[PDB]
Amino acid sequence: LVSKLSQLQTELLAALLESXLSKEALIQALGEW
Amino acid sequence: LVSKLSQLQTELLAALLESXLSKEALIQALGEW
């Protein structure tokens, strides 16, 4: 159903968070808005 | 220098944003805090 890209995006983000991704990094990514 | 993991994390996050990653998704990831 969900696009390949969309699916890849969601899976990749969960994988990062599971791996230890810092809040600082996410705050940095959100800042581009 | 930077750990393999750390390096992978940063590269992966930029790749996601470049690909189109939504703000909603990042807001969802930040929310776990």
Image (cartoon, coloured by chain):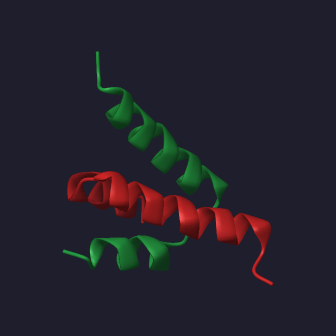
Chain colours: A green, B red
- Residue lying furthest bottom in this view? B1
Left or right: A23 as drawn, with respect to A4: right
What residue lies at 40% left-to-right and 43% top-to-bottom?
A9
For the image shown, how many numbered marks are present on the structure?
0
Q: Position of residue B4 (x, y in %)?
A: 77, 67
Indicate whether A22 appears above or below A16: below
What residue lies at 54% left-to-right and 55% top-to-bottom?
A17
Indicate whether B2 appears above or below A17: below
What residue lies at 47% left-to-right and 49% top-to-bottom?
A13
Left or right: B6 as drawn, with respect to B10: right
Q: Position of residue A33 (x, y in %)?
A: 18, 74
- Asked which quadrant contains residue A2, the reply is top left
Indicate whether B21 appears above or below B9: above
Q: Nearer the viewer, residue A4 or A31?
A: A4
Where, quadrant-wise, is the N terminus of chain B in this rendering?
bottom right
Q: Nearer the viewer, residue A33 or A21?
A: A33
- Residue lying furthest top in this view? A1
Where, quadrant-wise, is the C terminus of chain B in this rendering?
bottom left
- Asked which quadrant contains residue B2, the reply is bottom right
Residue A14 appears anywhere in the view? yes
Q: Position of residue B18 (x, y in %)?
A: 35, 60
Residue A21 appears anywhere in the view? no
What residue lies at 54% left-to-right and 59% top-to-bottom?
B12
